[PDB]
Length: 9
Length: 114
Image 1 (cartoon, rainbow over the protein chains, first blue to last red):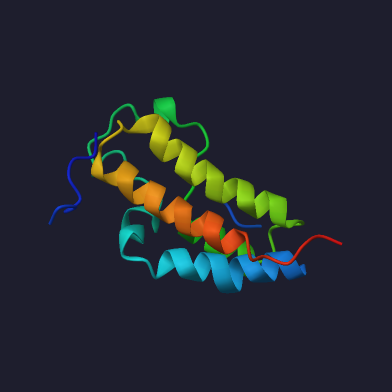
Image 2: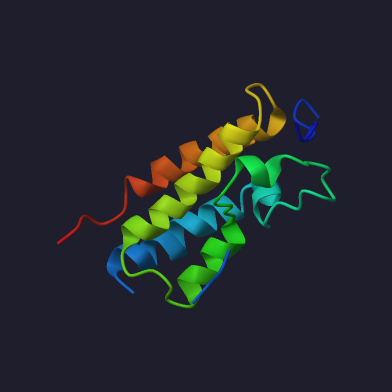
């Protein structure tokens, strides 16, 4: 996976 | 990712591409994936035909496409690669589904063939 992208900030 | 003009193609460039690029969830797709800096060893093993908005952008500017269907396929390859490589629930997948929804939406207002 690429990890989080800030969704859900 | 190599680059080298109908009413539909103009619409894809002026309306569709523009709409996705300005969207906040587009940054991960604005450039070709770099498996080393992103530490994704298996990426190019899984993805045989990478694609991104900048390549599409450049192909439209350099009149790479002969017909709209080619361009639309590139947009779809971009989404497909994302769904295939990543897991459901991942942030990037949610971002790609958002961008694809906006894509389908804009595409519906594209002028009809012939």
